[PDB]
Amino acid sequence: STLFEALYDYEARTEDDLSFHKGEKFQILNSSEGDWWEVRSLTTGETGYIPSPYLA
Image 1 (cartoon, one colour):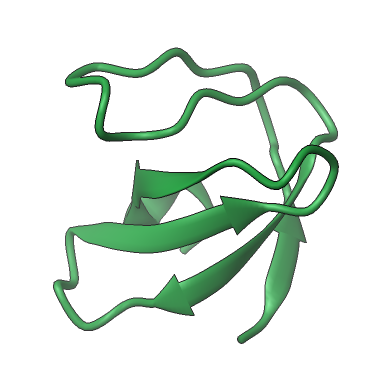
Image 2 (image 1 turned 135 degrees about the vertical axis):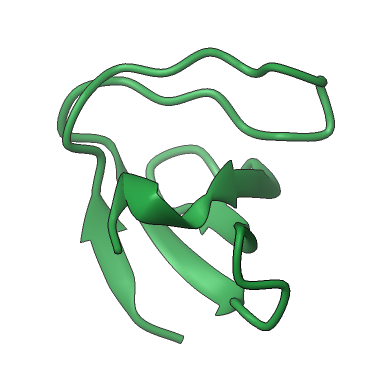
């Protein structure tokens, strides 16, 4: 349920994951898979996956 800003730019590896850019805002919907987390961007509204150590 918590939010975060992108620490550095990123570009989707499978295409079911989400791409990002320095200082873009996002929020976590689910973290339970440990390694990859269900994310949504707040700036645009795009939803997908990211690797968890991107913020954690």
